[PDB]
RNA sequence: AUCCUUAUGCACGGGAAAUACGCAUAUCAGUGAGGAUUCGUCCGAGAUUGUGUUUUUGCUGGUUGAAAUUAUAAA
């Protein structure tokens, strides 16, 4: 579909260009909406702002391929190079759809501790990320154990968030031990939680 | 190709190992990237190849289990999918 | 940094400053005394005598920057403006204690000497403090930090709402 | 002494498609700008640009 | 193991705005300026005096 | 004054002789040991009086210790 | 990378010979689009219809007009006498594919394929690159496969 | 190692060792000389001991030769190690469940050091329990 | 005083193993013959066990069987070392018996190249001129590629930082950098030596060559230029990918 | 006592002067230490004057330099102390040969010339 | 050489234009802090870098800004712009000198 | 007596850097360290080893919290 569609939309683009020429115009990238995130390379290429520089980036695919010998951490996308090709996939739709599948945001939240945070709506919030947190406290004279603990930490948040559905009958079966002084029953030594 | 499938499997396994320290989220992200790589690049080919499909099934399961293990020594009956598939931004892991 | 005095100038300003993304629009905890622009005399006059939208320019540090530091100058301005805000007339009087100490044709403040300037500043400070005392019933002894806060910001102050206080207490116990 | 990533080597262009939610805020802002009397003109222009 | 002198903060016209150990730093702006400028002069004067 | 490391020491005697014209020898070791380490200073500590305010001058004692300038 | 490519060009030329490589290219003033040529006739000249290379992996597509293939097979036999027919065994297929629809190792076809690969091997020197039978995969299309 | 680590002859000796390290932590290895697992542990600890030196100390106990300390583990008696500070027993919660003693081989020298470090820290704090940085839950 | 001696001998044992791993001889002088022999024997035994063990581990990994999370890592080190040994041994062998291309072969293949070139009628790629038309752009491209790696990461190690700094310098004093590059191309026949960390694509590994950050810039430039230049002149046939 | 073949040996004051000159040259980069460097200088022609160490043992390792000087008409001395010479050069390690090199635009040209003259006087 | 007794001292407490800079190099920046915050609901903004698309800017980019386009207000700092080592600097200087010589 | 050069020492002042900066009963080192090269030659001063700190030494200040708290005495 992508290759046939590429064939199509490039022809279309060419036609458009010809038309523009006939009517003396630079080709309006406003018109190419519809056939924008299609084609290989994408029509998003042609009107990227670094077009004329990337003209000289040649033997680029092969260079990318040969990164398996230069940079160590190894590349799950050696094949395409965003610049010269474009977003060769989209998965934005996917994120949207997954939420829907799990009864929308609200439903998802109702799994999580969220309502415990006691906000009216969710519009105004933000998370502090885990990687960021790790980074922040990895500028200190920390003995390896400490570092490990820090690394672990970004779970001791995730777990808590998902607590109220990692800590019920159906998820884990067994005891129901009372966390001391509190009406909070575990369903297992989910130690972080 | 068999070889590519094998490579994919290895990648999954790699992700799974070196997890002890590594966060659930990071691991999940890695998995996503690997799976995205697999899919975006072959696309058509996966739906035919049954072995690859099987691997994907199992790989995903393994990934889920790592998280489960982290959460509790005892394996659960089952989580909801929620924790795994909910997006990073709603506090999930964002497995694709 | 476009620092803004009012809290909610950010959004509209931000919108109008996408074209200059280098620029970073900062709110502030300081109740800065630029609301006392109209307490200044020449400026006020110019505002009055506009028949139209008029972009108008002033070295609000008139004869200052060759004599004292930029920061120093700004501090002085803050002191004076604050005083003006508190009670304009008093400030004016202070400025115009000596009629020999005139205001030039292109300035907005009474071209003093350095000792004189210092004295004026002191007077202004006194006015600020005394006025504050009169207003919000407080002993003028305080701490130097507190005094500084009062002058610079006239800020909200660490004013924990009753609820907050209660929460804190709970946490403590 | 893993050092900090030189701030100005942060990632810049060819980003993901802008989020509907995000866009809506902008739209709202522009509506406010417009509806709070016309500029007269530039508000409309700004909206168009957006 | 002495406290025979004391060590103060070496202000300048670039510090000026950032030192708070000595008082009056925004309180009495021009007084503060005088103090800091004066201090600087003394330092310079001291150097010159030493040379002399 | 001496620039190019003044003069050498075969047994130090030569150096001493050289110094002789300058003529000021043993005072500057009663300073140099106080600086080159402060062990002498430490010993001394384990004091010193100025012409203070209201000396009288019947009063005659002044110690020093780092939490406080203890006057007797 | 560039160096590697250049080196492989030498090897490519050897594989293709000067003449066939040239044909594949087209002329210098007006080069060809990958896999195309100018004429149907220059396509149908040498065996080597398409050729390509992606790094180490080369991909030569040969054609043969029955008789030619037979001749090649005969030559191969002469060089390497194959009485016991240890040739469908000792060969590679795409063990991925079904049983049914991989290279039917139909003796003659197998022989042809092996002959072709032998020829290819002969074409390039050893000392630049070991081209091994193990590593090669020589699908044959025919009346059979 | 045999030559690297110091070994104990009798229960009294062991007790003395446990008591008399005020500053350092004390890892004893209770194990039968000729066993695989025990040997491995000793090898690991040989490496670690020098490293951790200024904070911990490693010792060895032939459990068959010195049978005084079958109070410690109710006669389970696999080839274990135990952690001590100010003559208090120090409790290192892994997954395993045996919070008392690590009755299992760890292979990452660094990992071993880290756990020792953790326990030292715990001891200094005054804590009896300490959660290991690592999990385990494989090597029972 | 035997304990001390034993301890010493332990170190010797360790050190010969280390040497073997490195791939350096254990030509210790004052050691007595039979002890030395014993040590050698031990080392041999280790090798027999060690290499084989590594291979087994690798096989297991390939299978996807079950293997300890540190064991695999260990194997990868050991395996890497073995690979290195093999490669350097290969090199040594080559050195011993001359270049595997005999002259006739060379003549054949060189001739093939030359004739091809003639057929294609190829203007050779000239040295990057002192005032090259597409110089600056090329340089920029090179630097971008170098950067690429970091664009993600939030911390940097030291080497990485150094590299980044170099890149910045190149950007910021472009002319100077260009000059340096040119000089290197002209002259520099010698180089800071290259360390080879090994990869992890488990089912088959190797090799990541870490060149010194400075040389890298020059190399990058060269890569950019040749690939550009070749493309401009059609050195590479339509077929090559 | 110093070697006979080390000739011309300076006198004390002269020696001191020479060392001062050396020091000056060292600061101004107008000197080269070391037998081999001295030799190089001589070959070039850049040597204004050569300073050797009498207390070089084994003296032989210098005693080409004098010959070279003679054949190039560069004046030369030995000083007595190789340690001293080394120090002057700016080297803790003890040195045997140095060369004050030529350069018209030296501040210390005049001083150097004086020393050269002195050296010449010694020679005969 | 042994590891040091792990004690947990907090003695330092320093600050000072002079000392800030140094430490500014190691501190996370303000834009990095911003990045580390991710808006809650939204599909939060990612830069697809060819080597790895993974990277989320995060709440560095302002809502409105995000909706439109990029920012150089978040190219803020001079106090962590990767400077060379002593060695590296020296090497570069040497190279420059060589180049100059060649040019003559 | 006036002006300048070099080195140093003391300092004002202005900067950059600390991934740097030391130390050594060590081994070697202008009687050649380590490097260049157009291959003719050229530069000429540390190197090796061990090791102590090294997201930093010493000091100050604030806000805070911490919970931050008020002498005796006669009718």
Image (cartoon, rainbow, N blue to C red):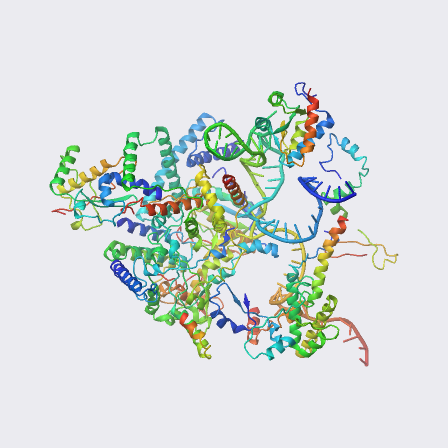
Query: Residue A110 location in percent, x, y?
Result: 39, 71
Please give left or right for residue F22 compared with residue I40 in the image.
right
Q: Name the image quarter holding residue F56.
A: bottom right
Depicted I98 relative to depicted L2: above or below: above
Q: Quadrant of the N terminus of chain I?
A: top right
Nearer-the-camera pick, B11 or A123: A123
Depicted H51 relative to depicted L15: above or below: above
Q: Name the image quarter holding residue J38.
A: top right
Query: Residue A185 location in percent, x, y?
Result: 43, 67
Nearer-the-camera pick, I173 or H86: I173
How many numbered discs, if any?
0
Query: Residue H22 location in percent, x, y?
Result: 58, 48
Depicted I193 relative to depicted I241: above or below: above
Query: Residue B16 location in percent, x, y?
Result: 37, 53
Nearer-the-camera pick, I138 or J12: I138
Q: Name the image quarter holding residue C100.
A: bottom right
Q: Is residue G52 in sight in this rendering?
A: yes
The residue at 83%/57% (across/down) is F52
Q: Is residue K14 in sight in this rendering?
A: no
Nearer-the-camera pick, H112 or K36: K36
Depicted K29 relative to depicted A115: above or below: above
């Amino acid at each position: 579909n992508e290759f046939l569609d590429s064939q199509r939309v490039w022809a279309e683009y060419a036609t458009k260009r010809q038309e523009a020429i006939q009517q003396n115009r630079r080709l309006a990238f406003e018109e190419l909406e519809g056939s924008w995130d299609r084609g290989i390379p994408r029509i998003s290429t042609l009107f990227q702002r670094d077009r004329h520089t990337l003209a000289y980036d040649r033997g680029h695919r092969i260079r990318r391929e040969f990164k398996q010998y230069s940079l160590e951490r190894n590349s799950p996308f050696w094949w395409t190079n965003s610049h010269h090709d474009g977003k060769l996939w989209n998965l934005n739709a996917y994120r949207t759809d997954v939420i829907q599948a799990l009864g929308g945001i609200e439903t998802i939240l109702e799994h999580t501790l969220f309502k415990g945070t006691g906000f009216n709506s969710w519009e105004g919030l933000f998370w502090e990320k885990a990687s960021g947190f790790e980074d922040s406290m990895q500028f200190k004279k920390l003995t390896h154990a400490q570092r490990t603990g820090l690394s672990q930490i970004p779970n001791r948040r995730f777990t808590l968030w998902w607590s109220p559905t990692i800590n019920r009958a159906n998820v884990y079966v067994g005891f129901l031990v009372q966390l001391d002084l509190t009406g909070i029953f575990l369903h297992g030594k989910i130690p972080t939680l | 190709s068999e070889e590519e499938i094998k490579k994919f499997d290895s990648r999954i396994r790699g992700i799974l190992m070196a997890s002890g320290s590594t966060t659930f989220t990071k691991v999940a992200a890695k998995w996503n990237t690997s799976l995205i790589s697999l899919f975006t690049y072959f696309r058509e080919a996966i739906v035919a190849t049954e072995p690859l499909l099987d691997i994907l099934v199992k790989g995903e399961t393994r990934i889920q289990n790592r998280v489960k293990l982290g959460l509790n020594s005892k394996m659960p009956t089952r989580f909801p999918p929620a924790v795994f598939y909910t997006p990073k931004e709603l506090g999930g892991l964002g497995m694709i | 940094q476009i620092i803004v005095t009012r809290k909610a100038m950010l959004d509209p300003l931000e919108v109008h400053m996408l074209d200059f993304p280098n620029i970073a629009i900062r709110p502030t905890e300081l109740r800065l005394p630029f609301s006392a622009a109209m307490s200044i005399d020449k400026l006020s006059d110019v505002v009055m005598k506009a028949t139209e939208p008029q972009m108008v320019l002033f070295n609000i540090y008139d004869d200052w920057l060759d004599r004292i530091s930029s920061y120093t100058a700004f501090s002085r301005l803050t002191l004076l403006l604050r005083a003006l805000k508190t009670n304009e007339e008093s400030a004016k009087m202070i400025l115009l204690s000596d009629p020999t100490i005139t205001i030039k044709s292109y300035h907005l403040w009474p071209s003093f000497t350095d000792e004189q300037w210092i004295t004026i500043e002191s007077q202004m400070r006194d006015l600020i403090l005394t006025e504050y005392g009169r207003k919000y019933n407080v002993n003028i002894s305080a701490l130097t930090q507190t005094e500084i806060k009062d002058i610079i910001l006239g800020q909200n102050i660490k004013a924990p709402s009753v609820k907050r206080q209660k929460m804190a207490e709970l946490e403590a116990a | 002494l893993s050092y900090l990533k030189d701030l100005e080597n942060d990632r810049v262009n060819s980003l993901s498609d802008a989020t509907l939610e995000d866009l809506q805020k902008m739209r709202t802002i522009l509506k406010s700008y417009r509806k709070a009397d016309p500029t007269n003109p530039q508000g409309w222009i700004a909206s168009a640009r957006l | 193991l002495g406290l025979l002198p004391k060590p103060e903060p070496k202000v300048k016209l670039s510090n000026m705005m950032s030192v708070f150990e000595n008082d009056q730093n925004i309180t009495d702006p021009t007084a503060w300026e005088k103090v800091v400028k004066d201090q600087v002069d003394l330092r310079k004067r001291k150097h010159l005096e030493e040379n002399e | 004054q001496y620039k190019f490391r003044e003069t050498t020491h075969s047994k130090r005697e030569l150096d001493s002789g050289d110094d002789q014209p300058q003529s000021s020898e043993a005072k500057r070791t009663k300073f140099s040991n106080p600086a080159i380490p402060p062990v002498i200073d430490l010993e001394k500590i384990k004091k010193l009086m100025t012409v203070t305010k209201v000396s009288l001058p019947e009063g005659s004692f002044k110690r020093v210790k780092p939490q406080y300038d203890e006057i007797h | 990378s560039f160096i590697f490519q250049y080196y492989g060009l030498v090897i490519d030329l050897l594989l293709l010979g000067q003449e066939r490589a040239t044909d594949l290219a087209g002329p210098a003033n007006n080069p060809n689009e990958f896999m195309q040529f100018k004429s149907k006739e220059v396509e149908k000249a040498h065996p080597i219809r398409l050729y390509t290379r992606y790094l180490d992996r080369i991909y030569m597509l040969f054609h043969f007009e029955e008789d030619e293939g037979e001749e090649l097979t005969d030559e191969y036999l002469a060089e390497n006498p194959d009485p016991n027919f240890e040739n469908s065994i000792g060969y590679n297929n795409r063990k991925c594919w079904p049983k049914d629809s991989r290279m039917r190792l139909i003796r003659q076809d197998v022989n042809l394929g092996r002959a072709v690969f032998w020829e290819i091997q002969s074409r390039v020197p050893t000392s630049l690159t070991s081209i091994k039978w193990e590593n090669a995969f020589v699908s044959v299309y025919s009346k059979n496969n | 190692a045999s030559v690297l680590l110091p070994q104990l002859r009798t229960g009294w000796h062991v007790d003395q060792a446990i008591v008399t390290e005020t500053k350092r932590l004390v890892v004893i290895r209770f194990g039968r000389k000729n066993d695989r697992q025990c040997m491995i542990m000793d090898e690991l600890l040989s490496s670690i001991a020098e490293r951790v030196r200024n904070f911990a100390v490693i010792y060895l106990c032939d459990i068959d030769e010195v049978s005084d300390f079958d109070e410690m583990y109710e006669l389970t008696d696999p080839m274990t190690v135990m952690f001590f500070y100010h003559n208090k027993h120090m409790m290192c919660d892994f997954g395993t469940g045996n919070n008392n003693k690590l009755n299992f081989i760890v292979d990452d020298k660094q990992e071993m050091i880290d756990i020792l470090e953790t326990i030292f820290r715990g001891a200094r704090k005054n804590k009896g329990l300490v959660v290991s940085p690592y999990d385990y839950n494989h090597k029972r | 005083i035997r304990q001390k001696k034993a301890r010493t001998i332990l170190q010797h044992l360790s050190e010969a193993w280390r040497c073997w791993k490195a791939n350096i001889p254990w030509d210790v002088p004052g050691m007595p013959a039979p002890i030395k022999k014993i040590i050698e024997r031990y080392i041999k035994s280790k090798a027999d066990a060690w290499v084989s063990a590594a291979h087994y581990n690798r096989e297991r990994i390939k299978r996807g069987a079950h293997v300890e999370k540190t064991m695999v890592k260990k194997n990868l080190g050991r395996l890497t070392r073995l690979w290195i040994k093999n490669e350097q041994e290969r090199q040594r062998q080559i050195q011993k018996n001359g270049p595997e291309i005999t002259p006739e072969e060379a003549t054949t293949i060189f001739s093939v190249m030359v004739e091809w070139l003639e057929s294609r009628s190829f203007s050779p790629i000239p040295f990057p001129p002192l005032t090259y038309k597409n110089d600056t752009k090329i340089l920029v491209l090179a630097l971008e590629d170098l950067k690429d790696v970091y664009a993600s990461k939030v911390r940097l190690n030291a080497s990485e930082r150094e590299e980044l700094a170099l890149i910045e310098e190149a950007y910021d004093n472009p002319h100077d950098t260009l000059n340096r590059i040119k000089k290197y191309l002209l002259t520099q026949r010698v180089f800071k030596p290259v360390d080879i960390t090994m990869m992890e694509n488990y089912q088959n590994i190797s090799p990541v060559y870490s060149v010194d950050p400075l040389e890298k810039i020059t190399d990058a430039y060269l890569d950019q230029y040749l690939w550009y230049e070749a493309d401009q002149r059609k050195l590479f046939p339509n077929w090559i990918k | 006592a110093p070697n006979p073949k080390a000739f011309p040996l300076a006198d004390a004051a002269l020696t001191q002067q020479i060392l001062d000159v050396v020091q000056q040259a060292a600061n101004l980069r107008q000197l080269k230490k070391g037998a081999n460097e001295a030799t190089k200088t001589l070959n070039r022609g850049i040597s204004e004057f050569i300073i050797m160490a009498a207390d070089c043992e084994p003296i032989e390792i210098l005693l080409h330099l004098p010959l070279l000087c003679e054949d190039k008409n560069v004046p030369y001395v030995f000083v007595p102390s190789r340690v001293a010479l080394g120090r002057a050069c700016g080297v803790s390690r003890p040195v045997i040969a140095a060369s004050i090199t030529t350069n018209d635009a030296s501040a210390i040209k005049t001083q150097i010339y004086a020393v050269k003259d002195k050296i010449e006087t010694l020679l005969i | 050489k042994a590891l040091p007794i792990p004690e947990d001292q907090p003695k330092k407490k320093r600050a000072g234009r002079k000392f800030r800079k140094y430490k500014e190099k190691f501190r996370l920046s303000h834009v990095r802090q911003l990045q580390n915050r991710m808006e809650f609901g939204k599909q939060e903004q990612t830069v697809l870098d060819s080597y790895g698309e993974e990277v989320g800017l995060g709440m560095s980019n302002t809502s409105l800004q995000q909706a439109v386009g990029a920012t150089s207000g978040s190219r803020r700092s001079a106090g962590n712009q990767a400077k060379l080592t002593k060695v590296m600097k020296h090497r570069i200087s040497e190279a420059n000198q060589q180049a100059d010589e060649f040019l003559i």
